[PDB]
Image 1: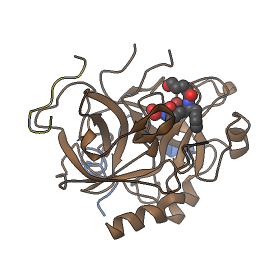
Image 2 (image 1 turned 180 degrees about the vertical axis):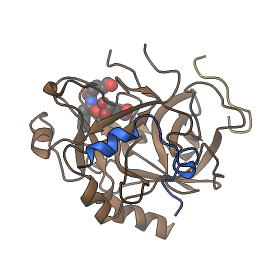
Image 3 (image 1 turned 135 degrees about the vertical axis):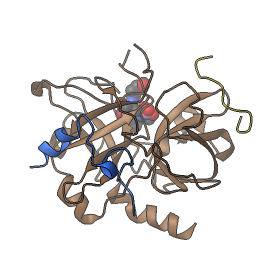
Image 4 (image 1 turned 90 degrees about the vertical axis):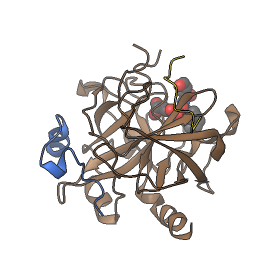
Length: 11
Length: 251
Length: 27
Ligand SMILES: *[B]([O])([O])[C]([C][C][C](Br)Br)[N]C(=O)[C]1[C][C][C]N1C(=O)[C]([C]C1=[C][C]=[C][C]=[C]1)[N]C(=O)[C][C][C][C]=O
């Protein structure tokens, strides 16, 4: 939850 | 960082965040020393007592960040790692002697207002600035106190380098020439320290001769955070500089 | 090369809020 999601390219 | 303050925008543009792919979490700090090399502490990647042994595909590097948890669209740059190099004589068995590692980026990062490399010291710069009483600056997204919890944005604190005998007499751990300690003494009034999550981040100083920022240390270890009569220990970058060069020159 | 000169500070001749503290300690 804590961390906002990174764009799908990297993860 | 304990007893620090929010960093200003672009105040530490070589600051790098080491981020675990899954689960998604902040592992350590690091620093940008060129368009394709990042410097950090070896213990951020390898520490067998806690069953830690990260490889290239396990991590990401986030550069040009301010906010700890948000994805800073159009500002931060995320990079994959090509290869990790840990000092061959990194001593994880005893006292974290030679706690340093280099990480080569898959592709070069483009510099901007928020992304820019720090300089590595030469013998003369180290000699002139690495003196007891002289202050350096540490940055990170680590814990705010030992045990709010963690900051919303990058924290900064300035600390003085401490005399080697005082560093030695503050702990039972065997100190080496590849480390130096910093922080305020109990009677000095002021406080501040690095804490859990700040490891691998840079201890920098601004040269008064050429007005450039140089990375003199890497946050390595400490026994608690901001405890009276205790000091933070940092990897002595200049003393391991020949190893840095050799890795970069060879790979 | 260009290392250690921040785009939003040194490059523009602007100082951050606490760098003076460092300088004053270099005696
Ligand atoms: B880092 O974020 O990974 C952390 C930073 C510490 C700030 Br205080 Br300088 N570095 C550490 O936690 C290192 C890695 C292994 C243990 N460690 C220590 O800092 C020390 C003592 C130590 C142990 C073995 C060899 C050298 C030093 N830490 C503690 O045991 C405190 C409790 C840990 C809770 O955070």
